[PDB]
Image (cartoon, chains in turn brown, green, yellow):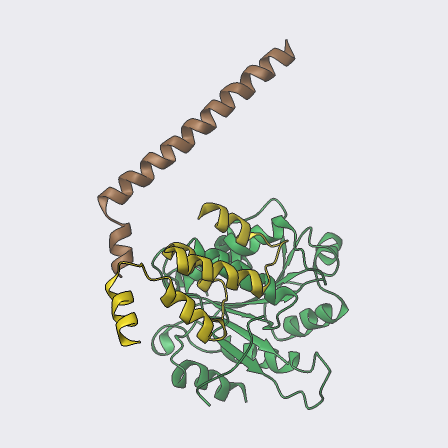
Length: 43
Length: 228
Length: 76
């Protein structure tokens, strides 16, 4: 119960949101590069 | 008598009554399970049992489908929140105990009567299901009959015989496509109880497939029986 | 600890008890509580792990300028 209460705090939610936004940025960069490569190949 | 077994399991051992019973069967020999099947076991059956308080009844042996079930349970637990632990009953052929590890709450030991033989327990296991399907869920007799469903992956001729016996006992069975022989081949070949698990279907949709197999009693009563 | 998680979660590779005990002793000596938690939680038999020599080594790992070491040598 104590660990669950700590995990559901606003600070932990904000930390997890920041980490997930970083993951989304990495995926967006990967998709950007792959789309550029696909456009280069198809032209 | 399966009634005594169920009464001991629920009352004298403190285990809560199940809102769903899922039986894991089959499993071809080999240390390495496919990653697709591993994901199906991890984020599928185990997740649905976690979210509906279901009973995972499977072989308690250290090899075969039981080891895969244990690994999936451990994987879910390590990536789990502060929720209830899944009761995983293992049926295989003094409060303190001594054993060598080199995740199952209960270890049903069936007296086959002959050392070194396997398969004599299966009938007993089926009898237990034939009891727990007829029991009322929730509180009192107002609840619906407890749903019991079998999920088959891989398998052999003995697993086919078990499936036939289960369908004789009005217990629904599901066969996973792409597993290999037995269940997968039978599904490709393809009475009311039998349900086909498409390879397109995967995790995050296990509960809907369970419901559509059970209904084939209504959907709403099953939903209110669970916690979703 | 992420490397340890990735290595120990692999299904293809299984780790024998000797490596688990060696890593557990290293973590206990070097004050890495997360590593000891991970190693013990992965099916480690702590009862067979501890030996009188291991406890003696753990107590010998006390700092030179520590009250525990001072009292231990004063008792002898």
